[PDB]
Image (tube, rainbow over all chains, first blue to last red; front, side, top):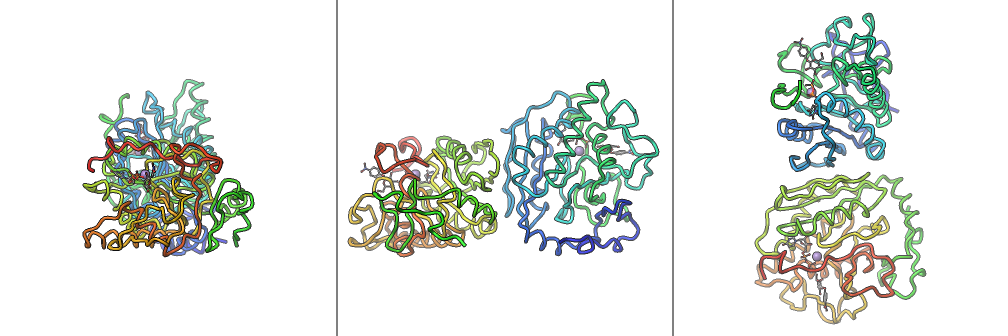
Length: 287
Length: 287
Ligand SMILES: O=c1ccn([C@@H]2O[C@H](COP(=O)(O)OP(=O)(O)O)[C@@H](O)[C@H]2O)c(=O)[nH]1
Ligand SMILES: O=c1ccn([C@@H]2O[C@H](COP(=O)(O)OP(=O)(O)O)[C@@H](O)[C@H]2O)c(=O)[nH]1
Ligand SMILES: O=[N+]([O-])c1ccc(O[C@@H]2O[C@H](CO)[C@H](O)[C@H](O)[C@H]2O)cc1
Ligand SMILES: O=[N+]([O-])c1ccc(O[C@@H]2O[C@H](CO)[C@H](O)[C@H](O)[C@H]2O)cc1
Ligand SMILES: [Mn+2]
Ligand SMILES: [Mn+2]
């Protein structure tokens, strides 16, 4: 049976947070033994899933670059299935995939508001988990399209529920976090509460856990609509509320989702994924 | 460890050939216990691959219908990867896939002659086996595109090396078979020799065996080119020469690849796959 000490050494990164108060590891470059994990997971013959949405001009701007980088960097050495959700399949870039990669594409309805496009992902992911993903993979990541894999994003990131530290807020105090602060929203987190600010651009876990994550987030999204309120950062606000109540069993350092606009400080040793520059004037059609 | 008698009962179909002189089964409807095999293979967690080529007009004519039917009928209940080779990826019909199905597409060079398009498949399949397929699947089938799955085509068809009985010739005397009969060809089979006439539209096996099948067939194809000769039925002539020398460990009945132009006689109990009607005048560009 895989124990934390088998693969995780926090002492390799003494100047950062490596363990939570609930004993979940925060995975930083230097702390993980990928060789040990690759061997362990290869013997289990795991398959890892990855969902990605591209609706509207997000397709032309980001989808090819995401998928090309995912092919190269995501869980290399293990079977991987990319689940691609687009509103227009005729604009799907059909890139060549390498060994142990395969994919499938689904046509989805485009929501009128970009905010609803972002939030509806929670409903859609859950539907696909029930319909097929639960039978296909051992672990699933759900990711934003507006980012690019830069280096190996491997089995060290796998767990029962996996959260991502948002690049801008990882050193901040909880009372500075951009949680939803209105008690009328289901995403509400009071001042004096909170562990971390999680980025909604990457989350994952077992199909069972991701199903619960997305189900509970979407319930909150629906409740808010009935109360004529919309959380400040939409699905991300709801995701943060979820992970407050249901603590992630693993957290990823900002190295796994880094914004180069910040620069590259000492803490960020090897970037695995980077944000694309925002292009809202083109890719979004409403305020 | 799986034994033939665990799943195969020849006495269920007494009026047809069910066993070869080398003790390989000929799989007919009624002889196989799919429930036993589905359990056996699910516990082994197998993945089955399927290669299919569509070049030129074959894409629009046959590819969608092939894939839609394969999605529905091929190895249901088990992970499947469709490997699609086309000369124009922009013409690839991106159908919706069901649970445990995924795919990837490759751009290939279109050969000038339809005969070479058919024959070059042997080279290309081998390259892909070494490159990736050997790492991705336990068994692989290689199929023509100009045919449609009609019913369950499942784990009862899997084996070390798998051959298909050609629908028109299965009752024929070997010396009436359309083997290549010129001794100058690598595919030459003398009168007085031959077991069955095998259809090049379906063959399969383990990646190791399929690699040998395709490598040896392509070596025969290249040798013939150096000797200024082309086998009468091209890759099929070479496939028949291969299976004469290296007996298949399993044969599929004409039920697994039936031409309805013959009609539907008593022997054909449940069609799993049917030929598309030939449209050479439209789909081919040279004599
Ligand atoms: O019009 C849209 C809005 C959102 N998205 C998807 O939802 C994700 C989250 O939205 P976005 O990345 O724009 O939010 P941000 O990270 O910029 O706050 C995107 O990466 C896309 O995958 C999309 O495809 N089309
Ligand atoms: O111009 C061509 C010729 C052949 N093929 C592929 O090669 C296979 C064998 O050719 P064909 O089916 O026409 O031979 P037949 O079964 O009719 O004798 C086809 O099913 C296709 O997959 C193709 O894609 N384009
Ligand atoms: O301090 N900044 O100038 C700043 C703040 C936040 C930034 O990223 C955005 O953060 C919000 C939540 O606070 C969302 O995660 C959003 O997706 C990010 O773009 C960048 C700079
Ligand atoms: O006698 N016929 O009318 C007749 C009808 C269909 C036939 O099928 C043909 O057989 C060939 C080998 O002989 C190839 O397998 C070819 O792909 C197939 O179309 C062959 C003969
Ligand atoms: Mn984003
Ligand atoms: Mn054919």
